[PDB]
Image: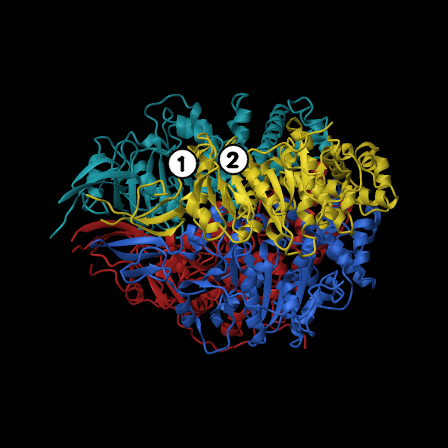
Chain colours: A cyan, B red, C blue, D yellow
Amino acid sequence: NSVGQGEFGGAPFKRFLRGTRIVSGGKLKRMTREKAKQVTVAGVPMPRDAEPRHLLVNGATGTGKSVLLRELAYTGLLRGDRMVIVDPNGDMLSKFGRDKDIILNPYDQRTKGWSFFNEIRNDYDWQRYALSVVPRGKTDEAEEWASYGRLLLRETAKKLALIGTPSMRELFHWTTIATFDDLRGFLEGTLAESLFAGSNEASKALTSARFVLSDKLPEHVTMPDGDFSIRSWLEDPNGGNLFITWREDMGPALRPLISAWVDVVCTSILSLPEEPKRRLWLFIDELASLEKLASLADALTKGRKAGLRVVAGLQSTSQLDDVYGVKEAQTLRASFRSLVVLGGSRTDPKTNEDMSLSLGEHEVERDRYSKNRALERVRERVVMPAEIANLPDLTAYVGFAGNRPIAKVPLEIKQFANRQPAFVEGT
Amino acid sequence: NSVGQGEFGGAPFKRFLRGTRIVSGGKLKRMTREKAKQVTVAGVPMPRDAEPRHLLVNGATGTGKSVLLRELAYTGLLRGDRMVIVDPNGDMLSKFGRDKDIILNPYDQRTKGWSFFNEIRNDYDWQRYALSVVPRGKTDEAEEWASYGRLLLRETAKKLALIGTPSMRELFHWTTIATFDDLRGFLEGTLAESLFAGSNEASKALTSARFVLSDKLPEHVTMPDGDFSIRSWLEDPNGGNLFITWREDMGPALRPLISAWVDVVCTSILSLPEEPKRRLWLFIDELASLEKLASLADALTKGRKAGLRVVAGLQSTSQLDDVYGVKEAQTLRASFRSLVVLGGSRTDPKTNEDMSLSLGEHEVERDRYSKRALERVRERVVMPAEIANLPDLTAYVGFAGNRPIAKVPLEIKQFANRQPAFVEGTI
Amino acid sequence: NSVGQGEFGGAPFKRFLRGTRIVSGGKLKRMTREKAKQVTVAGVPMPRDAEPRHLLVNGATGTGKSVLLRELAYTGLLRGDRMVIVDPNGDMLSKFGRDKDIILNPYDQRTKGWSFFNEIRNDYDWQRYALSVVPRGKTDEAEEWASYGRLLLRETAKKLALIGTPSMRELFHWTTIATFDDLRGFLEGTLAESLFAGSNEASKALTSARFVLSDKLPEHVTMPDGDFSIRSWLEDPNGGNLFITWREDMGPALRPLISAWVDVVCTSILSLPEEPKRRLWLFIDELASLEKLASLADALTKGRKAGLRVVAGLQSTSQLDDVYGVKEAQTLRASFRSLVVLGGSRTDPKTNEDMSLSLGEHEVERDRYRALERVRERVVMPAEIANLPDLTAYVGFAGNRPIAKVPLEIKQFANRQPAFVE
Amino acid sequence: GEFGGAPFKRFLRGTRIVSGGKLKRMTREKAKQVTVAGVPMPRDAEPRHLLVNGATGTGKSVLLRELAYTGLLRGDRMVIVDPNGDMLSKFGRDKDIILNPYDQRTKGWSFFNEIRNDYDWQRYALSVVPRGKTDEAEEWASYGRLLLRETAKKLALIGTPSMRELFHWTTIATFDDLRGFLEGTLAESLFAGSNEASKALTSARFVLSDKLPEHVTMPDGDFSIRSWLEDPNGGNLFITWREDMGPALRPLISAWVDVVCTSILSLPEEPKRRLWLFIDELASLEKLASLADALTKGRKAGLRVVAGLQSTSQLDDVYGVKEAQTLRASFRSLVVLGGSRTDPKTNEDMSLSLGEHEVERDRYSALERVRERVVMPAEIANLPDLTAYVGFAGNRPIAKVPLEIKQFANRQPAFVE
């Protein structure tokens, strides 16, 4: 039994048959090290091929996610990669913000002016981006109302754009403030003219649309108007990085707007002309803190050519499950091929079981000694749920995509100088 | 097998491989003892780093939760910590109430005057605190109604504030007493002017909003009006402590108001300027007795910088599950990194299993003697039956991080009544 | 293997490691026997500290629940305890009814006069007791209607009380017989004036309230009126005991009224001034036969100061699950710290599993002839409960106490009064 | 040697299985008994009911025939839900009653005959309008019961207690006309005043239109099932019907079974009385509102229910999983006659009901403690016809016993007219 020491937490064994291999952090760093310039995850160099297959970092609060994403971004920037960072409190901005970099925050004096009208190029872009502005509903019923919201939104905006008045204040006024008869009058000449009239059901549908827009649009209206386009930004090689920041006491109010930006990035990258040299990271702080994104799924599945790399954080399995629903949450999570398990709470035995199961089992041969020698085949978890619940901070399991063993690795708290103010209030 | 006895309830073993470690109460007290001034949980000093990661105390009635919370509050006060205490019957008030301390109870002569208007500073605070006044609905449909209630609430309140009459009596009158047409008229000029008019659905929505508000607002109206602000209180270093008390025969009536106050604390601490020295405790007596709090989750996840420490009590898993729903209840519980299991009823095998699972399993090597062989075995450190048969004033303490759990006895410290629990005013 | 024999039904063992301890009926009686005067559960003296933590008695029909509750009530009376007894057919009344005792039954000549109005003291009592009159809806939508029903009830009642006519006959007429417009007119001046008007939805809600009230109020109207107040009765030390009796062929008709009475007691004891000496028992014959009580949960958790002790009967887990819903039924059952299992049907393998799991497992060391083995097992298998002979029960008291299989003695009680009159 | 698995060296605990011979001797009693598959039924198990679970053609007819027979030889009375008047033809007597809207021998009846007190109107509207399958269907059933009782109370007042009139008013008369007929009744304003009230009344109408048709066609009269229950010399009741009419008559037959269920709860205690309720196929009736209470409170009255079931899913679909479980739990004695290989779930449920045992066994090359099913699911799926596992209430072992096909002479025409 000369295996599973300084790697495996269970009993050492004679021979490993099949399943998940677990190695020491040092040996994994040796296996994943590559010729080319790499990025690092918990000190471990990330396999180049694994980058575009995404990374999911699961762990409790204060277990080292900041340290991890912070190191991922730094090593990515050194390599000259570009990136969009969903940055709470502007922490990433304070430490990695350069002068050529962009900032999106309706309450930061340094923000660029924007409105979804700036992303419209073709006619098929109206629905495409109405999908970003109005994220998927939690329930089938709510997604029905949202559908009405999008029909009202794209047709109202399409017209405003035509009559030469593409303003969010005008759009918010029509879809939310104008009387029912005036809105219906304005809708005359658009594809929504008769769909929202003629019966009590059509009226109910319109009412649902109004309520949905009155919830999503407010922050789009207060957002400083300008000509910045995330699409164009994505096309500009010297555009720098984009920081989507916001104060934590404003999370609920800005959830729809920030979801909208994250989603605009998700569909937009699908339109980028093939470029083998492009590497763009999407740092979604806490995935379950955003609304139910319409384009995230396709971006995690068809972003390889555009060079999209997504890094998202997750805490409890139930969080995402509640936002996307069990089935879609499973589909979403399965779209990140690389996983990092930072350890959870003893009070969440279910998620610890989910992460333990994800890390995987192995089949092994062990010597069952007796004293007055027998070989036993045994299947066991490489990482027990309890080992996850008992992990000390700054300690993570790294399971890269493909045929790679996992490893328990410690996180180094690198210090970063604050090269920019996180938040600059003003008007 | 010279290891485990005196600590582990099962058969002693030769070697501990992995999983949850169980130690003696005494050895744990020695491991968690720290140089800095600490607070104690069931006599065990709580690791300083575990404090801002919250504590979940689970147990049946009369198992010693009072003794535990009482000791935790006492040792915290000795250290000079500030705290908000959801205090049923004013028990904590009578034992720890000082003269400079605050009391919130619509029926106590000592109460401070308050209305949610006192918490509004910026415009984004209207929705922020409407979320506190109208907690999350139990079902998706009920949350739909609650959403209408908040729209009506925040828009009617915003106007009343403008016309100089920010009174709850007025707000309650408009949203509940005024005729439909009069309300609609009053709403003219507000963002809700057209949302609640123009169709049967809009009228239905408005009706739902009225019903929701007629349910939540009553006690806000009866509450003695004044200038007290929980936000300002949180900012005042010499503000003392806050005791949210109430008579148990008025639990159902005050559930919405008390939930509002608890939630106000939860969002508000997210606006506090970073102060490494600040330590605020939120003692939520019985978490599942409050409504579905909208800000609890974020407060449990982003309150570290503000120095928030939450201590909540729970009994049956099904209780919180019914209030928040299985998914959100899981996420909520998972936010408390430290757990204390006080033992439940034999008539609740499911919760005993949940607590047993939470305490965790361990993998161990044991000698199976014969008339000698080594065997590897995985088992629960604490069986469900051990929890059901726990004697009162006995608890399992499992602190956050890499620490062993321990079965510890609770000492019934005696506290002198330094203040009357309830000052109703009637002869 | 010396340990086991005469206590544990499985194979005898060498050493007990952890879990549920099972002892002999006699050894349990010795352990629970105390100096103070006690009550008895299946012949076993109930620990004093366990009483206010409630007792749940689970078993099929004819397994001896009557014998058990009868003995409990008797030894409690001998001790001078007061009690409310949900009494099907007036059986407990005929055996234990005293002259100073109270009877609540719309169809018995000895009943006291009552209306929920007699329970109102403060303004917060209208909602408090509307919750007693209109129990929780089975489904979330039914509770929506029940909410409308309580709003209509408390507001129509609050007004009738103000204009001097607090009669259930008037209330029932307004909430159910008066026309929509007349009712709407009556509601003017009340907090429900605008809530039930102005839209189709408000009208739908009002219609729902009427239907809910036409189902719950019928029996409150036929109830002989009088001045009896359960709250006042709870405060009177010399009030005696309360017997809520009814004929079993009127179960469905009186379910709402009896549920209201049991609920009234449940919130009311929470208003009682702390009295360390008070000991009130609430005998709820069959918990799942009552409606979804709004205050039971709190009474089971906050009635310690008031000295409330609840004893409830239950059969199949599915019964309570269907009334409260699986989540609240679990919370409710989890509120009774002491359990008594009387043996179920073999056609109910789920409940026998539930009870078995509730009786618990133990981990033990046994000799296998010779070597030592560690084993986890159910102290009481589901089959053992299904095959329990009548008048045999497993008594598992709260706290750190072992369980025990005990036989119930069929004590004979003389009929001291007619069970039903008129 | 009676157990199907490997023989053991010591039975520790659980369900015991004995030979059919030993069980029959164990349950045999001095007092006259009734037999279940040739096994004398413990006198104390009788009022705790019997559930007979089995496939089609496995012996249910034989079993129920022998039980009804031995019960008759003892003087017992019984209400028998009798498909195709099979029981009637074999055991019918001149004094015996018959309820069948299409048989010339039927008695005259309308639920009006059961009303003696004001609390009976709701009591028997429950019988006439069985519980709805879903919560919403039970909502409509509720409206239909409010409408029924209020319209019937008025009709009886105005001296016209007619099912034809009732059916006309609740199903045929116009909306407004109905409304107007409802003034002066408790239903007066509940069904008027809004769109919800109308929608509700409309539902009530639909429900009644489904339940009442066969009550109207039923030959009217003065037969009262309550009075019959009270008359010691009333004989036995046979509720018969042709199988090609099961769906059409499900409402009526269900009503009669429910009427029996509530009505015995009103009977003055009589330790000498013994009444059997033979509910052929429990899941073939509608969801009975009173059945559960009859099974739980009919001891004093002397009620003994014998019900048949097949697949677990059948009752589950009628009463729902929760209520079905409660219902099956009310029957303390069980009989498993053999099922289909295609039904592994019910076979497992029956296997689980027969119980497990913990046994000590010699593993010849030491001891070994094993928990196992006394009767495996496969053993039930492979049972020959006329073979059954009998498991009586209380502490008694189960036994596999053979059903003997006795022949009964046709003493009466099963159907007439």
Disc number at residue D379? 1
Q: Quadrant of the C terminus of chain C?
A: bottom right
Disc number at residue D311? 2
Farthest residue to the right: give it. Answer: D158
Q: Disc 1: which chain?
A: D
User: Residue C258: x percent and y percent?
Assistant: 67, 58
- In the rendered image, is residue A69 in sight? no
Q: Residue at x 62, y 56 (%)?
A: C293
Q: Does residue D36 sit above or below C411 in this rendering?
A: above
- In the rendered image, is residue B220 in sight? yes
Asked which quadrant contains residue D260, the reply is top right
Q: Nearer the viewer, mark 2 or mark 1?
A: 1
User: Given the image, on which type of amino acid does mark 2 rest?
Assistant: Ser
User: Residue B245: x percent and y percent?
Assistant: 57, 66
Query: Badge 1 local density, few (<14 within 10 Å), some, or many (20+)?
Result: some
Residue at disc 1, secondary structure? helix
**Gap between marks 2 and 1 measured at Cα:** 16 Å
User: Given the image, on which type of amino acid does mark 1 rest?
Assistant: Glu
Q: Does residue C289 sit above or below A205 in this rendering?
A: below
Q: Residue at x 23, y 57 (%)?
A: B13
